[PDB]
Amino acid sequence: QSCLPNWIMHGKSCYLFSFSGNSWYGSKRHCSQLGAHLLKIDNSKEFEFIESQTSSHRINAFWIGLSRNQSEGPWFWEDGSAFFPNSFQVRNAVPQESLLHNCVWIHGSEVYNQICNTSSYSICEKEL
Amino acid sequence: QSCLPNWIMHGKSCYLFSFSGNSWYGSKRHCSQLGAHLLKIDNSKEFEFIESQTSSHRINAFWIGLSRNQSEGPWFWEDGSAFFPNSFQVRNAVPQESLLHNCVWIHGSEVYNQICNTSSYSICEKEL
Ligand SMILES: [Mg+2]
Ligand SMILES: [Mg+2]
C-alpha cells in the first residue's frame, strides 16, 4: 500500500515525524487533523523502527499517544486502549513534586512523562 | 549517529526523500547545497530500503544519482563511479526515438531512464 508525501512507510502503518514544536495537546490535534493519531507503540518490532529514527534525531524529543487523566491514573493510548510495558517502561522525569507530568514523549531510546503543555516534536501514525 | 531533521537514517547513510518537483539538474544542485548528493544505490540491501519507500509513494517518481553524457554511453553515479547492475537494471520504457533520456529515476519498484529536465521528486543521500 501507499503513504502520503513526507510520511514514512513501515510495518502496518504510515508515520510522520513532525519536526515542529507543539504541546502534546496541539500535537494530538495536528495528527487528527490529518486523519491520524499520536504514535501508538504496539510491540517491540514497532519500537525498534521508531527508536532507529528517534535515536538518530537526539536533539529532539517526540510526543507520543500515551497519556493519563491525572497522576494517580493509569496510562492509556489514544484509542483508549490500556498500556502494557511490552516495549518500554515510562521513565518518571518529574524533578520534585508534580501532578502535571501526564503526557509521554520519546527521546533517543527512552520514554519519559512530561508536562502536557510543554513544547516538543511529535510522531503521528496512520494504519494501512 | 544523527541525521538532519526531516532526513531518515538507514545503513551507513542519511536520506532525504524530497517531495518537491525539480529537473534532475535542480535535484542535483538541491542535494549538493545540503552537503549531500543524489541517491547512489550501492547494493541490494540499500535498494530494498529505498524501494520500501518508493513503492508506497507511486503517484510520482524519484530522481537518483544516475545519468549518462550521451545516449550511446555508459551510466555513471554522481561520484563518477561506474554503474554495474548488481541491484537493478535500468528499464528502457522509451516510446519513440530520443537522444535525451539520459537521467535515471525510480518509480515504484522499478528504475527508468528519462529526459533530464522533467520534473519529479528526488532522493538525496549523505554517508555517515
Ligand atoms: Mg502502532
Ligand atoms: Mg548509497
Image: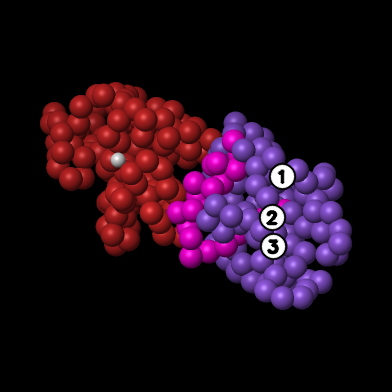
Chain colours: A purple, B red
User: What amino acid type is highlighted by mark number 2?
Assistant: Val
Report the span colored magenta.
A45-65
**Helix, strand or loop under label 1:** loop
Mark 1 and ligand 1: say if the CB distance to the nearest ligand atom is below 8 Å.
no
| Disc marking residue A85 | 1
Q: Residue B90 at what x, y percent from top left?
A: 29, 26
Crowdedness near tag 2: few (<14), some (14–19) or many (≥20) residues, C-alpha within 10 Å: some
Q: Which residue is mark 3?
A: A92
Q: Residue B104 at what x, y percent from top left?
A: 30, 36
Separation (CA) of disc 2 from disc 3: 6 Å
Picture mark count: 3
Which is nearer the eye, A67 or B66? A67
User: What amino acid type is highlighted by mark number 1?
Assistant: Pro
- Chain under label 3? A
A35 lies left or right of B21 = right
A40 lies left or right of B10 = right
Residue at 30%, 36% in the rendered image: B41
Separation (CA) of disc 2 from disc 1: 8 Å
User: What amino acid type is highlighted by mark number 3?
Assistant: Asn
Q: Which residue is mark 2?
A: A90
Asked if disc 2 and disc 3 are in contact, CB closer than 8 Å, the reply is yes
